[PDB]
Image (tube, rainbow over all chains, first blue to last red; front, side, top):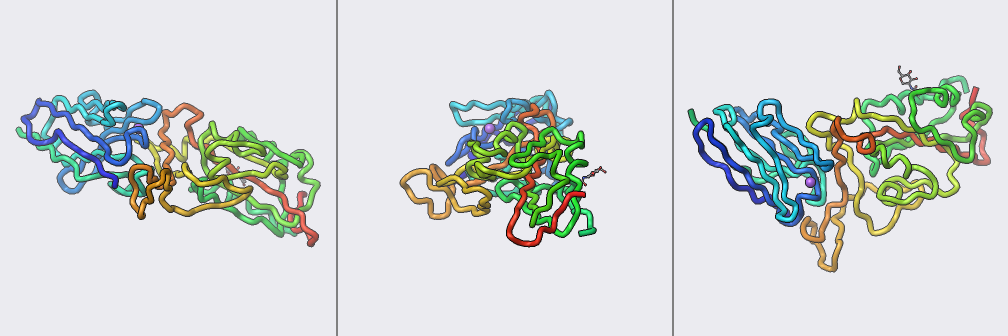
Amino acid sequence: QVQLQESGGGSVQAGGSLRLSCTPSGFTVHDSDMGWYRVKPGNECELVTTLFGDGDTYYADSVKDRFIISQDNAKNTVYLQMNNLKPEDTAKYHCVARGVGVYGMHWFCGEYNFAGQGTQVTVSS
Amino acid sequence: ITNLCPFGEVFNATRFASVYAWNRKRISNCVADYSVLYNSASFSTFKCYGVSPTKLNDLCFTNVYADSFVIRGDEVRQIAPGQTGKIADYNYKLPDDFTGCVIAWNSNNLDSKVGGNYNYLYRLFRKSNLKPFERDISTEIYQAGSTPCNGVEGFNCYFPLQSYGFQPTNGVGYQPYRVVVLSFELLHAPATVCGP
Ligand SMILES: *[C@@H]1O[C@H](CO)[C@@H](O)[C@H](O)[C@H]1NC(C)=O
Ligand code: NA
């Protein structure tokens, strides 16, 4: 069985922070590059971040320096630290294993990616 | 033999195959100017075995095969006789006595994407090594232990393919390289692919 255990979302006021935690079950964060997509109102999918194998990071221009991805291999967990949140950050956030890997050939947001249920984030006025 | 051999469709294809599902094109009934390719400053690898590139224009073969795919830059060394590693072992295997040329060039500008391109795959698990020129496109779950998998990925139950993650700021060893392997076949049968 393969799955992602996701936590840390919910409701927060603008200017606040959240921390998402994502732990694979049946495989590890070492198997593929980990990241997050977010599905904004209107079913608008956007790649938020990815931690590449080489240790480099991608961020969407709109979240750079406010959001930080990190990984703890020993804990088999990847984290998204979300600071200084804004109303336009409201979305369903989806941890992903990018690409094809030991967990199978899956799709998310039109590309190869293994997602799960995700975590709603709602940022109020 | 008046037509020019259709190499452009191979070398200039918009999309390349994943290495596990490497493409093969038969070239026949045509005139090939190998020297023009060889004296192309377009290639960072142009390595021939059992033939001289400076003499290939002199020779006729029965058929030529042009195999193509993408791999990492630090994997191009595996596309040669006598090599080991996940590409030679489980994806694309040359024979010890290969007669042909291995051609490669950096394709970061075409094959990387911002955020990562994961559409190029390689086979990471296999029960045995490929024989020379074998192709395996199967996707059965790899049973790494003594528990059977029942078609479900999980602990010691691996889907056998893996994405490369090509993103533009990868170091050059982790960048995508396009590869063409030319093999030269002489049967006891007429000979249809000549140099000028
Ligand atoms: C591919 O296109 C380039 C660019 O125009 C051309 O110069 C080159 O000869 C082509 N390669 C082959 C194998 O025809
Ligand atoms: Na990883």
